[PDB]
Every structure is written in C-alpha cells, then in structure tokens.
Amino acid sequence: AGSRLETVGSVFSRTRDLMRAGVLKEKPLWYDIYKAFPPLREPVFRRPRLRYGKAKADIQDIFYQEDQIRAKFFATYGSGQKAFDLFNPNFKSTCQRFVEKYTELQNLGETDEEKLFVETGKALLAEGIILRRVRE
Amino acid sequence: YEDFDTRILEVRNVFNMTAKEGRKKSVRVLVAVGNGNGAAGFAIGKAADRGDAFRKAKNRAIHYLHYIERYEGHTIFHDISLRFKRTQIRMKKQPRGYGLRCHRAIITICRLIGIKDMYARVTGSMNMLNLTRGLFHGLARQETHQHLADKKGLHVVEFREECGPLPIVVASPHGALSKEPEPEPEVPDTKLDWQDVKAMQGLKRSVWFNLKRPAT
Amino acid sequence: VESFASMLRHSPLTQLGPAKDKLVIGRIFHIVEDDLYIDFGGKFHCVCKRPDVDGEKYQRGTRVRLRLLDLELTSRFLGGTTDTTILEADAVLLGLQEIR
Amino acid sequence: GDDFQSRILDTPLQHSDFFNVKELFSVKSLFEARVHLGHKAGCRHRFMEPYIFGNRLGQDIIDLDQTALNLQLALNFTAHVAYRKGIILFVSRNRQFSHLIETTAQACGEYAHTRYFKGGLLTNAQLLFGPSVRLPDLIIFLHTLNNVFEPHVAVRDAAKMNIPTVGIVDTNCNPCLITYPIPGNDDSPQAIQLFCKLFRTTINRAKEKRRQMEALHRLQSPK
Amino acid sequence: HFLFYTGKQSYYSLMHDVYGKVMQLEKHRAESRDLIGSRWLI
Amino acid sequence: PMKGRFPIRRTLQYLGRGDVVFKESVKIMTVNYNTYGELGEGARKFVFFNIPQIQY
Ligand SMILES: [Mg+2]
C-alpha cells in the first residue's frame, strides 16, 4: 500500500503523509537524509504551460563590450587566417589580440572609433600579424 | 489492510461488441477506500464478471491513497469551491455536531476519510467519476493553518462565539514572526456566490432545504 | 578564485562570436567506415566524410581544420512547440592540420 | 550495542558535509568540462529558465553557480544513501555513453540500466523479477530523456514508487519530478565523463567511510 | 550482478564484454578466415 | 458568482455598515466628480463604495 500519485505533492510529502495515516510502518532509508539535507526546491509536479499574449521569458542576451570591437574586426578582416583552437583554455586568436590592443589605445584616451581601428591595425602590422582587409 | 474499508460508488453493466459472442459483457465498477483517519483513495475496475471488477478496483485504489487534512480531526480546514469538468462542488467548514449534509456519495467518502461535520452542494453534472475525482482534487489541495502561518509569517488566531473574545492561537510560524500587519482592505474584492449570499439576504429557501434527516 | 562570469567572458567560445564561416581545429575521436566524428571544442560533435586525398592519414587522434556553420542543427516544423534537434553540429572538413 | 548502531547511522546527519564532497568539484572544474553549454533557445524548456545564465548568440548558457550548489546537495544525498548501503541505479538511454555508464556502475559497486526500459519495471517489479525483489533506493539519471526526446519512463515511474531521483537536467529537460536536479550539459563527452567520475568517487568514499566507522565503533565494544 | 535491473543480465553482460573488446581493437589500430566450415550458433 | 465588481456592495450587511445619518435639514446631496484624473481618485471611490451606504 502506497501513494502512486506523482501529480500530488512530492515523494517526501507523500511518504510523510502515509506514515501519519498509519499505512507505512517503517521509514525508508532515504527519508531521514532528505529531512536533514533537502533539495533547494520541492519536487512537485507542474504542467508545463505555453506563454500567450505579451508574456515573455527573462533571459539576458550575453553581449560584452568587446563584441562591438569584434563585430567590426570580422566585418573588415573576417576571421584570422590562423585557425581557432577551442581546446586550449588560454588561446589568443588574432581577433582577441586586436581587441586587447584596441582596449589599450582606448585607455590612453583616444575617443574616436575610427582612430582606434586604424591605429590598432598599424600596431599589429608592426607585430607581424598578417591582417588582410578582405572586402570579399 | 484490515483497518481499511471499501465502498462502491457506481456499477455499470455494459455489453460490448467482440467476435467471441458478437456482443461481450463488461462490468465497470468505481470504488473508494479509506481507513477513516485521513487516508483514502478511489479506483476504477473493469472485468467481464462483477466479482473480478470488484477485486481489481479494490486493490488498485489501495495504491492511490490520498491523505486528507482534517481540522481538529472532524472537518475541512476551510471552505472549498471548485469545478471539475462540468461538476461543481462547494464545501463548507462547519462546527462540531453539524453532521454530514452532503451528496450521498460525498457522505460515503467523507466517512472513509474521517470527516464528521461538513456541508457540500453539487451542481451541474452528477457524473460519479467527476464528483469523486473533483472531491479528492479539492480535499487534497487544502491549506492547513500551519501552512498559512508559515507562508505569511503571522500568527493564525481563532475566535469562537462560544468562547467570547478569547483569542485562540491555532498556528504559530515555525521560523521568524513578522512585524508587518497583514493589509486589511476597507472593502474586500472577494467573489461571492449568490447561493451562499441569497440566504443571508432574507430570501426564502426551497421546501426541500434543511429537512429532518437521520443521523449521518 | 575566478568567477564564472569572468570565465565565460574570456572563454575561447565567447571570443569566437558567431560560429558561421569560422575556422577551427578539431580532433577525430571516432571513425565509422568513411565517416569521421570530429570534436572541435563545442557541445556537439560534427560528422564529415573522409576526403579522397590522403584518406589513410585521417585516423583517430588526428587534428584537422574545419569551417563551422552551426554549433547545433535544430529546426522547428509545423505543429511543433519546440525545435527539432539532431544533436549534431555542422562543419566542413578542410584537411589535416600541419603539425609544424 | 544499540548506541553503536545509533552512532553509525545518526552521527553522519549532524554534519553539513560529512563526506567532504565539496572538494571533489569546483566551478572551474565544471567549466573545463563544458558543463555550462546548453541547447539552442528553441529547444528550451520553461522549467529550466531559472537555471540559465543567459543566451550567448542562440546558445543558452547554464549558470555554473547554481550548478555547484545543486550538485553539492545531490552528491551529499548520493553519499548518505550509499553510506547506508542503499541500492543506486544509474539510468540513461544515450547510446554514446552506454558503455561508460555501465563501467562506472560496476566500478562503484552499484547498478546500471542503459537499455530499453520495460513497461512496469518499477510499478510491476514483482511480476518481472520475483516476489521479494528489492527495488532501487536511489536512481541517478545521467540522462532524463529517451531517444525520442521524451522523458525517460523511469522519471514518472520512480516518483510513483516514492524513489528519490538525482538527475542531470539540461536546458531542454523537465526537472519538475527530479528530486535533486543538477543543471548542466549532458551531451558533451567531457561533461558526462566528469559527472560519472564524481558519482563514482562519492559512492566509493561513502562506502569506505562506512567500513571505517563500523570498525571503530565495533572495536570499542571489546575495548 | 550490476546489470540485474535490465531484466536480461546475462545477455547484456555478454554484449558489454564484446562492445568493450571492439573499442580496444579500434583504438589500438590479415585474413579473417581462421575457421572454415563453421556456422554461428542458432 | 455574483455579477459585477465588488459584489459585496450588493449585500444588506454592507449597506447597513454606513454610519452617516444626515440631520433633518439635509435634503439634497449633489456629487460632482471626474472619471479621469489623479487628484479625483478618492471622489471616484466615494461614488463607487460610499454613495450606496449613504442613500440606504
Ligand atoms: Mg542535452
């Protein structure tokens, strides 16, 4: 005898209730553990519903300030001819070096975006990076 | 399960079409079970023989035992109004000695649950399954006084007219007691039922209302 | 201890930006006949076909070059409340990476 | 005598982290294993939005700060269950990781079911396994979806039998019936490999801790 | 047996061994007709 | 469900809660209120909630 009603309450609440009624005479071994270290949320059934009208989710689009610079670099030079290595946790791509230098110049106090874009290209050219201004 | 009792609520004897005899026979039986101490459940059993339908429904219901919260062991914690499909139920919490003034099927289940004093009205369709499902749906989703004290953080106080102005503390918040008084509106926006209000407005009831009946 | 917000900002995947028409390095971890399963550092692997040239070179552990298109192939169809995903990524195998 | 049995079983519940599961993992360790990568926004379940840090260009990102909190609770619960000699069943239907999960269960000393799940396995176990079959005391769902992108049958059936479930839930999953949800990536081999390692070390520590606790208390009885 | 709850512990225990063998051979890397006039068991 | 908003206004108990019983001199009470605005909210609520009690 049990409560195979998984849409009312939770495994813990149904086990608590069954013992109060007098049907379950021995506590499950997982019961005392749940009482002492419960989950953050109670595991109760809820019917997923759809959103209607003007209800919307609340998920923040992840856009950092570097993305403004990165977008320009991809539009002007595309992706660096060197291939991304996403297995190296500290990989520095050609675009990420462009954004690191672009930031340094902006710290000096340059206020014109055009100035920061052409100066960074010159600095990387001195470094020896091959930047191709591919309109294609 | 000697402490549990089983009660029948509906028995349908229907003939169905199958190649064995052209039209085969089938018995669908809805039952309820309860120990009279808060634990109760219902199930539907089908078979070709009535005895088999009784066994299937009786042992299936013992696997679907709800636990129903009773205020002081004799009544529901608060008024309950709900519509399950086209079956409307309207239950009311009552004082001791009031008895079970409810649909005969609700009296049967309430005895299994252990409720001793309550009023209920059923309107719309009288479908036995919708009434049984709707009854357990409302009785198993009711809010005990302790739950209300925990949710709002305030004391739950009770005022009985036979005890005068004496305040009775029925539930105290488990954690931290709040200090912000619960907002008291000047005029509540509660949605009232004409049937409940009509009585207090002085309107004559039916000749069938509040007749003398045997103890339930 | 670095925060998760810092890790995400400085992550190689965050630096990639959009994954369409990007160049990445992958590693072959599983081969089934002439189909190569390539892990390029994303959530889902891609599956390409063994090139005719230097076919024997593409063995397990071999690092290759790819041109990403999608990180996950998903599409909603009529009468569906959620997107249908095939649990796979889209990329074009360009050839072996020079060890140098 | 009775005090010793009470000491073995009642003392572990007086400490917040009796098995010191906190050290096994860290937010950085989870980030290396790509545990923060979720499905596209179209595949998102409504009950997962609490756990999602945001949407990075169409790909939902899973907050690894909530994952650490939830994973801590799930690992602690899995340890106390293993400490008390409960049966733990690993369940998944992902065929890429079928052999890995069966190897993990065998290493832990527990059970794995990575194959087609028969209807009634838990709700009708006596007919399938025998009259006195003991059901699992905990089910760990490394994957909570089957191969038709529907909830694994054992998620609902484990709730019906009042079995707690520790499950890995991704952005397209429904965590409502999972007792201890662990928000995280379930598709990447590096994410699944990390979770399998954590569950196996945690279970082995709890089993070893029980052996040591029994010897100490047992030795005291003569001594 | 760790595969008891599958319901076919002996069938799946054998399919576990043969699948692990296949993986080690594929990772590690002649005529296969070592035996002739033989059939697979029914 | 009783029709309208705040159906409690249509109960004898609510109508009897009014405490303003005018002196015999009072013969007419005109109420000038605006349906839109911010400074006239109390006036609108007075017509909604209190005028029935006064008339009763
Ligand atoms: Mg997934």
Image: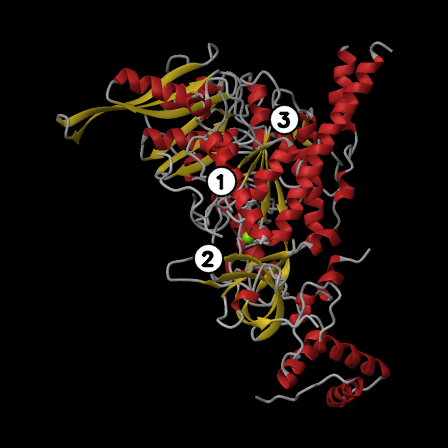
Q: CA distance from mark 3 to mark 2?
A: 38 Å
- Please indicate, yes or no, whether residue F29 appears anywhere in the rendered image: yes
The spot of residue D122 in percent (x, y) is 48, 29
The x and y percentages for residue B20 are 15, 26
Q: What amino acid is at disc 3?
A: Gly
Picture quadrant where residue C81 is located:
bottom left
Q: Tag 2: residue type? A: Thr
- What residue is at 77 percent from the left and 42 percent from the top? D22
**Is label 1 in a helix, a strand or a loop?**
helix
Q: Residues within 10 Å of mark 3 (few under 14, many from 20)?
A: some
Would you call the spot at circle 1 few (<14 residues within 10 Å), some (14-19), or many (20 or more)?
some
In this view, the mark in front (3 or 2): 3
Classify D177 as above or below B210.
below
Residues tagged by mark 3 and mark 2 found on one chain of the structure = no
Q: Nearer the viewer, mark 1 or mark 2?
A: 2
Left or right, residue D223 beside residue B132: right
Toward the left, the furthest residue is: B22
What is the three-letter code of the residue carrying label 1?
A: Leu
Q: Residue at x 49, y 40 (%)?
A: F12
Residue linked to disc 3: D86
**Could you tell me which residue is drawn at 74 percent across and 46 percent down?**
D25
Mark 3 falls within which chain?
D
Q: Which mark is residue C82?
A: 2
**Which structural element holds mark 2?**
loop
Quadrant the N terminus of chain F occupies: top left
Tell me how far mark 1 sits from mark 2, CA to CA. 54 Å
Q: Which mark is residue B36?
A: none
| Residue linked to disc 1 | F12
Answer yes or no: do the residues labelled 3 and 2 have beta carbons within 8 Å?
no
Q: In the rendered structure, the residue with mark 1 lies on which chain?
A: F
Could you tell me which residue is drawn at 60 percent across and 25 percent down?
A16
